[PDB]
Image 1 (cartoon, helix red, strand yellow):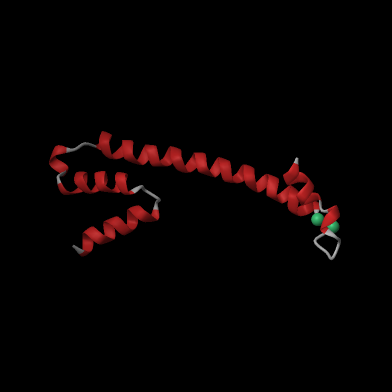
Image 2: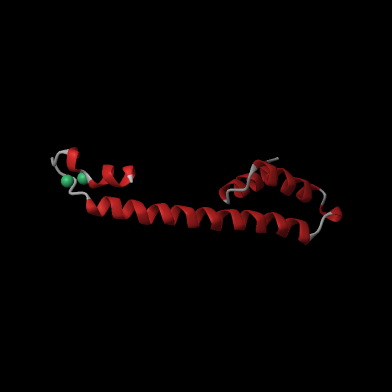
Length: 89
Ligand SMILES: [Zn+2]
Ligand SMILES: [Zn+2]
């Protein structure tokens, strides 16, 4: 009950998909018939997913930073905005 909910809460904190969470719950309730290989495979898959998303976000971050730094951000007419020009290109 409560401990089970806490377990789930902890998994969600790590971004595990509902599918992986369901699998972790099955291993959790019937440990005598599951192995470290199974649990680690679940962690590893999620780990690869996070590292991949991180790479994507940092890439967007680098572009956004350049767009941001190049624009004066003032009353300057958007007819001359570099951000619009960049997004067009
Ligand atoms: Zn400007
Ligand atoms: Zn601008």
